[PDB]
Length: 98
Length: 147
Length: 145
Length: 198
Image 1 (cartoon, rainbow over the protein chains, first blue to last red):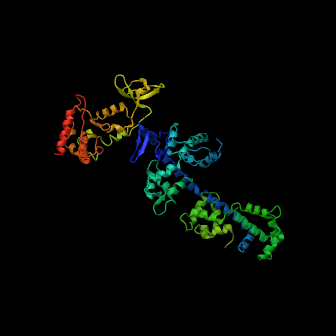
Image 2: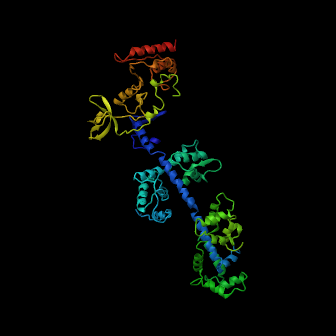
Image 3: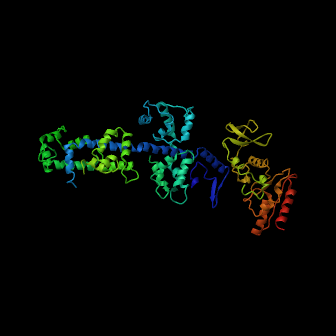
């Protein structure tokens, strides 16, 4: 399945019951690619983490952000409304409903 | 490009605590992540030093340097492939089910490579790991890529 | 405005509009108050309700008047959502001093004086931040339950 | 390291310390530039590719020399992973130079036995070695050539093995020029037989 990728000669090799067969300097080629991939390494998987790590910090100094507002505005309503005829009405009436 | 996204400038006004429209160089790593970019901390460190910029001494910023540094980090978002994130953790635990034992992921995320504090590690496992001590990383990496 | 909340205001509009023509006049206000037990409802109270509108109280004028007074109105499920995030372990009502500190230190809407008014009719538990849930009830439907 | 004990004293001439290895295989390498090349005085010396004349090549040397030689006067160089390979035939670079060079390197390190396929190459030490060591003899006893480092007793034991395992007769063909020192080996092989099955 792996060899599925790569801009490599799908000729130069050959598989069998216990191992793959390869022409020259191939495995050599492999490694090289590999070599580059370590210079990179982990390093990429770290980052995201790091990134992500702080991304949750914002939601915390941050998560709360809106739940407050919701609470914030929500109260204010009431303070205004509770004195409104129409709203008292709805209130006494709100129960007879179903 | 603008697509001129002027909301990056409005988010710089939410991270500058002095209101003078400058953001210190130590905040630029976390604000690139809050604008939708995940550069690794060594990469943020290199680039800085690369440009003979010292994050060791006092720093200020201007929007005119932070904008092109976010645009230089934005090309590196092609490194964020979720196949390799789930396959990394699938090679980290035996059997055909995606579960890391609690303390394996916590000690690896704090001590391997770019050190994440154990406070941040507990805030990233909180809710996805139940009392069985087994973190399902199929849903764990799904929720980590939801932010 | 969610659609079930707008249907609740449509049902309240139909119970106050007893002529069923689509416009609540002053006679509908007085006959709805008399059917709730208000035999002494003054005409000046009915005139002050009509003085909050620029035109006749049809369904869209009643919705815009309630919209402009309830610009921070929150349904009970979203208030309990925010209180479950403030008590993320579930079940427990949160402490009095924790809600006073977190209201002030996050926002200007959570300043103290306002916190003394929150404790003042929202009783102790509610005020204190220990109970929970009764305050969500009285924010969506006022007065003591 | 752990393994090697049997030899112990011979070890250094058979195999290298597990870090000597490690320090050698795990080192910086630039494939696209590192290469082997033809050389008028010395047969093939190593160098780094500098430029490219479209079908000519200019290379630096290891000693410091610059030569512009044909495209096929230039030969790749194995990744460090193949430093002092027991079996050159495992190399991914089957050249003329790489073979010369492998032998040479493990010799400068005093390893006289290196395999090249089925062969068992042997280089004249020109000095004394604890290899014919009476400890080794045992060590190589009952071991496939993959369970132990390149050595003649490997060949010689395997023969024996194979002899009883397959129920076939065996042979060992020793060959080299006048000064290669075959008698020496031959003799040494012979003792081996006599000892291990007398």
